[PDB]
Amino acid sequence: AANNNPQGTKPNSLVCANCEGEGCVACSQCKGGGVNLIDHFNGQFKAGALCWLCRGKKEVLCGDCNGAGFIGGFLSTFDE
Amino acid sequence: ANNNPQGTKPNSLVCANCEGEGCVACSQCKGGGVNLIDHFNGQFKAGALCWLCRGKKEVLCGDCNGAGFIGGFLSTFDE
Amino acid sequence: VKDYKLTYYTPDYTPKDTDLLAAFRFSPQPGVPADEAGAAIAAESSTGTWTTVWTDLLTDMDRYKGKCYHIEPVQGEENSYFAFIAYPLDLFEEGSVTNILTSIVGNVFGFKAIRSLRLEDIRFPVALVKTFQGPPHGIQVERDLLNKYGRPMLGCTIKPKLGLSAKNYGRAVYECLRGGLDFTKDDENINSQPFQRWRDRFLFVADAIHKSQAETGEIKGHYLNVTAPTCEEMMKRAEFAKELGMPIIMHDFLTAGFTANTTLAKWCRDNGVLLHIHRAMHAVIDRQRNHGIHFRVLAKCLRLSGGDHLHSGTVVGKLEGDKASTLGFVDLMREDHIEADRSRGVFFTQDWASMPGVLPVASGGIHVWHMPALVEIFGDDSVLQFGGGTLGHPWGNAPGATANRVALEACVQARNEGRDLYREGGDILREAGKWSPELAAALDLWKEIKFEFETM
Amino acid sequence: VKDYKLTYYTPDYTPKDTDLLAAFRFSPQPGVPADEAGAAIAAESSTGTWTTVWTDLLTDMDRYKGKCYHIEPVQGEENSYFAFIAYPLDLFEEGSVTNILTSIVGNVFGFKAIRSLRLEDIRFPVALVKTFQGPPHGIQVERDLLNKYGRPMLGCTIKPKLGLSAKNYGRAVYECLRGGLDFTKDDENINSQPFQRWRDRFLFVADAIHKSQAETGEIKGHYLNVTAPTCEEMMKRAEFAKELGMPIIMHDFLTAGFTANTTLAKWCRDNGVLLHIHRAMHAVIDRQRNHGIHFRVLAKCLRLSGGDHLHSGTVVGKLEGDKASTLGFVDLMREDHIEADRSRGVFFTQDWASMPGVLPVASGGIHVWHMPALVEIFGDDSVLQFGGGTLGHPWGNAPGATANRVALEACVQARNEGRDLYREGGDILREAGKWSPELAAALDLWKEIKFEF
């Protein structure tokens, strides 16, 4: 995505890198625009309407900082 | 007899005042079992059973109350 | 005691088949030997003496005595030893975990001449296993009650939301259960708190369960948290939850205790509900590798006291130094005969005497790209909880459930056909995420992992 | 809003009077700052997020999250800090201490970016203190029930414990109590083993109590262990011990749990029984100085949940530092208002709102030569448990009881007149052991006189 690291913090602090500590990133199908630009399936989603992924919000959750802002805890890692 | 600390053995856990046996020899009748002099009011007269051990010739150890080792719980939790 | 070998360290002694064995890992203070420390650990957790001047009136002695029979060093660590000691069977009450704990680990962990002490394992004889109840139902009975064969079960905790009304809570539960999940879990902090009392929560959750189960066609549930301040409040919550017709409840066995957990397990056995155990406040006892009580001991004590599901932790991220130990104590609570294997942490050979097994629950920040791994490690006798990997789908609650369901079915169906699950995980998921938009969006949101260049 | 601010470390925030404060001592991994670690401890033990993308869906947040407000470092130690955290009041339910435990010390101890974490103190607001029951009776009511004024109380434990029939148990208890002691204690491993069941032990102990009390004129007692495998068995044992007429029972609050302890405390309040709390299985949680839960937090949680006596351990042989801390939390068990004094371990000012006290108990291998020190440190609001110091006398059990009784009375009478007990305690013991043979034998057996400064 925006960062190709598997799951990583900033150099020292615990703040997440991919989301920059916001918890939400910009859609990668419409590039924040909000409308399709190519048919993405057989005929289910045609270009010129709401983006199929973000449904028109231009923002999605982040993958690693799994909604949180850092890289510990019951949200972004495994229980031992 | 009267030593300063509870006194573990050198580089060990065993009690010293008894060398691990748990009981010591009475320091009043010298293991004899019979009094030597008058003690309180002439009520413990020389010639009868020792007033401390009462003829058993052995009393309990003091630093290690029969435990035999020091760091235990019936001999140590006065720290 | 003397040059005489302490009367407690008897290396030529072999234990009976009705003795409770225990393995401590200890590290002594500077200037103290190892054999004396072993004998002292043996004497502290029993009659607290080496000599014979107290426990000798007429005959009673050496019967209620914890002989120590093996001391060895630990490879790699310096100044650290393993002490195997063995207790008789007449010291322990019949049917009480509290007594076993209070007798073994009562006041030995405060020994002064020991720098640190850990309890690594324990072995209950069959004669003692058969005086306890065990889990209310087990694995086969619980799999038959819910009618879920073949695949592992799915669940979704609602963790990050707090301060929600009771009706919106019921609504989220309904949206998840309708979409294709099996269970749903209350946050363990939720109790009768002023913004959300318990009876309202129970009512609306029961309504959601009935609706979704009637309009879907299979059996669905929700772990209701019945942890309470007293015995009376707890039994009252449990009775009301049974009245509504709920299949499963919840409890945590470390803040509430073992007396309450045993009482609740007997009630659940009488009334036919399943019990899900949540391990909270456990890192306070078993995180540091040099002091405390390792967790496999508590897993055994829970299999004895009662419980059908148990949180065990995932192993997708651990190395082989700890993945091995976790797989070890996961086999310690499903099978019926475990052979000693020190590489997997099992110290003694344990035979469970046809007592049922418990069910491991793998949870905590997992998503779709982990599904190939889990289905390969835990097998299909387990439960999978998806905290954030479900409620965060780009367009709702029910689509996330549908995505996870599709991924699990694809992975299982692929494993049945002989295909590998460490080389072809990504392939399976990508080729399945082509006739379903939900799984495509889910695959696009998270990121692949590629565990270790081909495998593990 | 970005985590260049952390939204949780608000240093100028002043905590309200209805907020629950907690003080952690933590040590972070090599490469993590201190402020980030404080904010992460505040977020782990609450809604586990720094961001508002998840919770604040509908204009509601900031009222269910804790916030760090002070991260001072530790003097002397290297790479260790203190972190103060303040939790709102509407996160916890009333009357439940299991909820407080599972909400503060839940998963925070399993955090990965922390090398070690310990919980040192905690402050309950009065708003929350007032919803718990507290001790069944307290201190004043207990002294009035037992009718013993102006001196500590005396108790003895029975070490021949294992493999001793119920009738010989009763006879030993009778000998001890007849000599002059007040309480006898039942060992903490003895519940219902096959060699000695509980009903036929309660019987003979009650018989001995009735004999010795009708013979001496005082009020005698024996702590009867009611720790059972279930709620029903526990209630059965307690009801039987009440029917016989026993004035005090025993329990273990760390192996049996807090639910069972609260249940038993409510029963004991409704039925007029006193409750003595034994602290088995505590070093497994609070020995190491760098991971666990300090014992004063558990003492506070106990005073809230219920209990009349509490074991606290001797303080005579602790040199300093770790001694002044112990005294510290003794003041957290008897007083009503305790000002902050970090030298004695007390971190926050605690006000108990006229809730009763709890009685300390000292034990662990003390003999007659320790009588002055104890009587000067703990005062007169305490119990003194003797192990071998009573059963080891060369003459028997009743002489040992008489010896300890005489020594205690002498030390108390000497303190009343205005005599220093640290300097001339042994002098008092020797001047008293002249007209009594038992005290002389005792003074001659436990050779260690003292450390007289």
Image (cartoon, coloured by chain):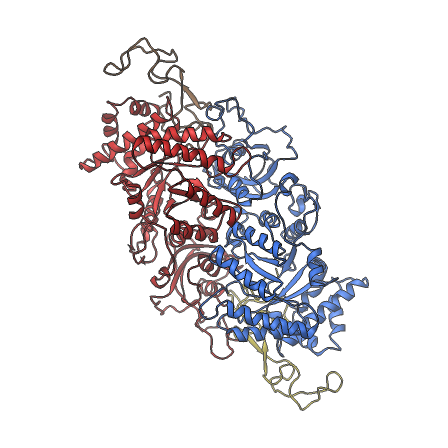
Chain colours: A brown, B yellow, C red, D blue
Query: Where residue C124 sits: x, y (%)?
Result: 37, 60
Furthest-top residue in view?
A: A48
Out of D190 and C148, give the one closest to the viewer: C148
What residue is rendered at 31% in x and 23% in y? C438
Residue B62: quarter of image:
bottom right
Q: Would residue C261 be found to the left or right of residue C382 on screen?
A: right
Q: Is residue C209 above or below residue D153?
A: above
Q: Is residue C294 above or below residue C18?
A: above
Q: How many marks?
A: 0
Furthest-bottom residue in view?
A: B47
Q: Would residue D46 be found to the left or right of residue C206 on screen?
A: right
Q: Is residue C144 visible?
A: yes
Out of C257 and C284, give the one closest to the viewer: C257
Query: Where residue C133 sits: x, y (%)?
Result: 38, 56
Q: Would residue C179 be found to the left or right of residue C99 on screen?
A: left
Q: Is residue C131 above or below residue C282?
A: below
Q: Is residue D373 visible?
A: no
The quarter of the picture where the C terminus of chain D appears is bottom right
Furthest-front residue in view?
A: C243
Furthest-right residue in view?
A: D417
Residue B29: quarter of image:
bottom right
Query: Where residue D186 sits: x, y (%)?
Result: 56, 65
Out of C51 and D319, give the one closest to the viewer: C51
Query: Where residue D335 sits: x, y (%)?
Result: 70, 49
Q: Is residue C428 above or below residue C335?
A: above
